[PDB]
Amino acid sequence: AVISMKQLLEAGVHFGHQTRRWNPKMKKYIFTERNGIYIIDLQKTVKKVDEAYNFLKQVSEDGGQVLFVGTKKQAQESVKSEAERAGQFYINQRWLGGLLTNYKTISKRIKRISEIEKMEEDGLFEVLPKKEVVELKKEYDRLIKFLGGIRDMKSMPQALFVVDPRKERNAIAEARKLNIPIVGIVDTNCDPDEIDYVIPANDDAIRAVKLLTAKMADAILEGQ
RNA sequence: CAUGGUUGUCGUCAGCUCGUGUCGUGAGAUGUUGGGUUAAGUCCCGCAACGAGCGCAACCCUUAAGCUUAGUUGCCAUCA
């Protein structure tokens, strides 16, 4: 559950953002400033972390899944790797506006993937007009790009893991509309009230994203 | 100038809309905007939009060249 402090300042977790870009609601979680950068208090960080850790093992033991998001490029592979580690579902590309609120139309497109995998094996990708061969292939690749990691999600996820709340604000709006708890990693200049389980950690360092989402992946691993 | 049916017209112009979702107290908006491109909301990239339908293509006829079948009532090369 707890992460050693040195594992954080080695991962750049203490790093925040410039004083220029600062949300004054982070003043509770900020510990002084270095080189004009608001250094997050690692103690507070760890504390908050080991509390979304117990909530997440609760979700995995109940049977719920966590929708990993983090379309940000620095979080892209970190989200993908640790979600499949836990058998959860991840988002790595453009968050489809209304994939949770408008699941009615998204459900057909999600099942379209498994449907598109079907015509290949039932033989109508073998008999096809020349342009339709690539046309239906193009429809596949678009869908794999977005609904690649959530193709097995059937209903609304019982939990959602946001890497950067400010970046993927479109996802948080859907979650709050359907009462979906969010575990989020806030660096600075982010709203700590738009999410419920707050991780005060750096959001740009490549290893910092990996280290915290792995512990959150460890949370599910100790629940299933 | 009660109408069915049929027709011109803008104009073969490329637009016209819908479902679910989202924003807006509301009329309304989005998608149908932006970066390019096309004869074409034609197509791509992105984007609170995700998908559709009537539209535009294509599909259908004729034409332009070729190959099989066919030899009359078509044709006339090898020959009289």
Image (cartoon, rainbow, N blue to C red):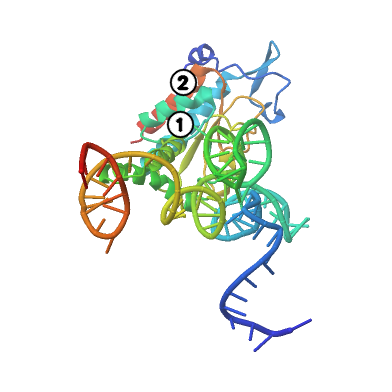
Nearer the observer, A90 or B80:
B80
Amino acid type, mark 1: Tyr
Q: Chain of mark 1?
A: A
Nearer the observer, A42 or A96:
A96
Nearer the observer, A100 or A132:
A132
Q: CA distance from mark 2 to mark 1?
A: 13 Å
Q: Chain of mark 2?
A: A
For numbered disc 2, what is the local secondary structure?
helix
Viewer can see residue A132 = yes
Amino acid type, mark 2: Leu
Q: Earlier in the sequence, mark 2 or mark 1?
A: 1
The part of the image, by quadrant, that contains residue A204 is top right
- Residue at position x 60%, y 16% from top? A15
- Label disc, if present, on residue A73 of the rendered structure: none
Task: Provide residue A134's location: percent of width, then percent of height.
Answer: 40, 38
- Residue at position x 26%, y 46% from top? A122
For numbered disc 1, what is the local secondary structure?
helix
Q: Quadrant of the N terminus of chain A?
A: top left
Task: Provide residue A103's location: percent of width, then percent of height.
Answer: 48, 50
Q: Quadrant of the C terminus of chain A?
A: top left
Nearer the observer, B79 or A224:
B79
- Label disc, if present, on residue A53 of the rendered structure: 1
Dot 2 corresponds to which residue? A211
- Is A24 drawn above or below residue A150 in the view shown? above
Task: Provide residue A153's location: percent of width, then percent of height.
Answer: 40, 43
- Is A164 drawn above or below residue A205 in the view shown? below
Task: Provide residue A165's location: percent of width, then percent of height.
Answer: 59, 33
The part of the image, by quadrant, that contains residue A82 is top left
Query: Do discs 2 and 1 belong to a common subunit?
Result: yes
- Residue at position x 69%, y 18% from top? A18
